[PDB]
Amino acid sequence: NVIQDLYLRELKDTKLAPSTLQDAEGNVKPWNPPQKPNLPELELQGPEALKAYTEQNVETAH
Amino acid sequence: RIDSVSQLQNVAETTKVLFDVSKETVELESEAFELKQKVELAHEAKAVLDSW
Image (cartoon, rainbow over all chains, first blue to last red):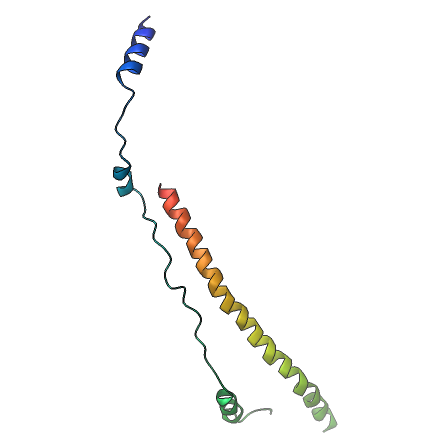
């Protein structure tokens, strides 16, 4: 009765509400791509380090 | 003196093994940098999606 009146009135008279995707964007985090896929740095090239190291530590066995 | 000598004999070979082993391990970490960037990408994607 009154159930029908409200049901009818509500359903009919509102069935669109605001909904803008752009407004949503403000409220959410932005996708941005990773940075620095940097390849590892190469170090201690040559036996220069090794010859230095054999000499450098006097105690090679004591 | 013989006791001292015997130790050094075995060492001489085996140390070369460790030498290689250490560098091999280090190589795995180079590849781990590629992994690290994957970990990052997953975290970012999930985070933006969670906000959505």
